[PDB]
Figure 1: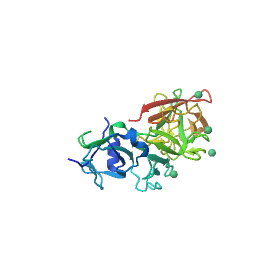
Figure 2: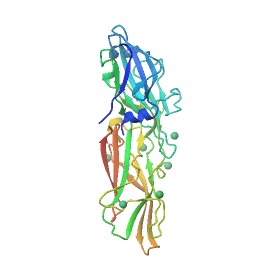
Figure 3: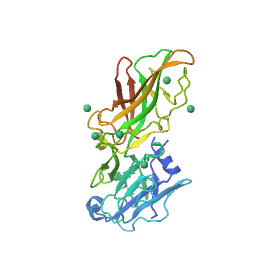
Figure 4: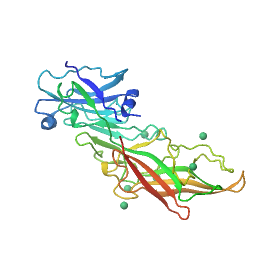
Length: 333
Ligand SMILES: [Cl-]
Ligand SMILES: [Cl-]
Ligand SMILES: [Cl-]
Ligand SMILES: [Cl-]
Ligand SMILES: [Cl-]
Ligand SMILES: [Cl-]
């Protein structure tokens, strides 16, 4: 056989099910001689596939413009990204701009972070530039290109809060607001992802940053409250034993990472601004509320790491001003 088969590797919800349900993915393919990709990439353009739309139809992955493996000893190098962008010149669908059809070498992506619909529309940009899909022939893997997508952004999986002591029965803490303070020259809102070495760099000639406080209050999983007259839309974070989540189970933030896999250089390069109420019972229908707003919380160094899931656990110290942070990290797989 000579037709090119597609497969997407499934990890032990999966990335694959998301691609199957949504827009699928896009493929770049560069045909070289037997000499290979590293020898010839410098003067090779995506001459075989340029943003080829790969979609799932019932039980298999397919593409419309059919292509065949070479009859001779020529090789094909593949790259892939997701979610697919149907307007790659402007980034209508995903705010993804691709390197041109006549650009030489490994491709690039210019990506902008989607802040619309209260952060609920952010794209989980995945790419594939692993060597096992480079220098492929019909004999490489039974004529099938197996893609393995990696998360190239940073995930803020959750922000959890708890007091440092048990508040007893007559006092509760409610979180009502949260902002991210990105500094002025730290967090990119627009950046270039390079498939050559799987790294992010600034846009040219001038870097594009988040330089103002970003309000996350409507992103938070706030619910109605009716506690001793207190009825502000909030999250009860009173449990001292287990920190209470501010994001819902299905919601997370996906940002262009800071310093790629290294994260922030210093503690407080990135900060949080939190609002919370300490409610003490007076009667069943009345209370005393202590409202703290715009309280600064510095995030630790080596945070917002590429390919990492970060969960921040905030401990509100009841005998002081202080809010201390734990950056719990996981590999984003
Ligand atoms: Cl936006
Ligand atoms: Cl800064
Ligand atoms: Cl501001
Ligand atoms: Cl509710
Ligand atoms: Cl609770
Ligand atoms: Cl530090």
